[PDB]
Length: 438
Ligand SMILES: CN1C(=O)[C@@H](NC(=O)c2cc3ccccc3[nH]2)N=C(c2ccccc2)c2ccccc21
Image (cartoon, rainbow, N blue to C red):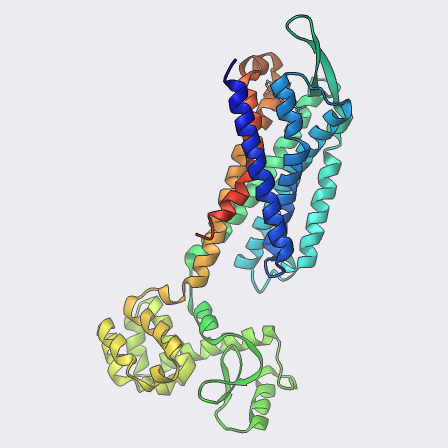
């Protein structure tokens, strides 16, 4: 009528600007900063390229013809615009699947999913996504043609239309898209983000706690006391000799290590350490009573201490050990910070003490809080993707099954806005990235 074209020009041109500006920004930032190019962002970089492709090679050749009600570009543009639209949706859907699968590797199988975290594999997947997406979509250029129709005053026009040899094939193709663009990617990412979510809920434990407090040094080093240490805080000898640490090292890893161990030997060593700390708590007649009275989070604070100072040194925390057993957490927290231990390693001690005072992991939660944030962003991106793409795919499927119904309900402004919703998905992720560093 009179307004509809105005709102269309408005919304289309706005969504074009945001999507062009938004995605080229995301690309130029990522191309600029080598520090930014993580595995997850290399995918979000392949995602932002498909969003740019959809935005420049399809959107004008949809608003302009839908605004004029006449596809006035060539038969080639008609095959091109349909080709890139389906290629884009495919690349995007399988980029989102790759992301869910790499975060699953990182969060759920960290020391077990080593290759899924190589940038070389990441660019292998990205290449296989674009190549296969152009391949399975070749029906669109093969079977899309100008379809002549006639307007008001018997005025010939064309519409760009995708027509397969019959109805069984038109309907088979939509079953196809249903499967490899929604069902199969949908469950893959729902199982994945579901497992990721389970893990992230179970939260911090003694191992993650000691990994934050100790770190990883592959080569022999000295701690705050000046003692020779390796791996994840593994004390080698109190003696000042370096020859003796190197000896106690080779004996513990079983090979002539030459001062240097692997990450895999550090974790094996570190697992024996947490084992040994916990056995020392159980075998010591002063520590075991306190331990049993402790809740699992505080148990881990007691283990944290015993891991740093040994069974016997901690068992001599007689006045703090008593307060803990009596559930006097504030008293214990105040007393423990008057100790020499506090004075030697304040930052670590302040955390362990916070754990004792509150019974929570707040002291160690920062990193977990970051992973949870990213994961919730990714689940939001996936849900806004499907919500932006279900309508147009459902309108094409309904056309292939009952074209007369589909066209009478959707032909005017509804499919105009349904198409608009599609392009909106390509300007969604940059806006999300903006609201993420708030
Ligand atoms: C030719 N082509 C369509 O026919 C359009 N479907 C409609 O426009 C439409 C559906 C419908 C239902 C009821 C009534 C009226 C209807 N119109 N489908 C997309 C597309 C979507 C996903 C993958 C590939 C192509 C597309 C995108 C850009 C250019 C051409 C193009």
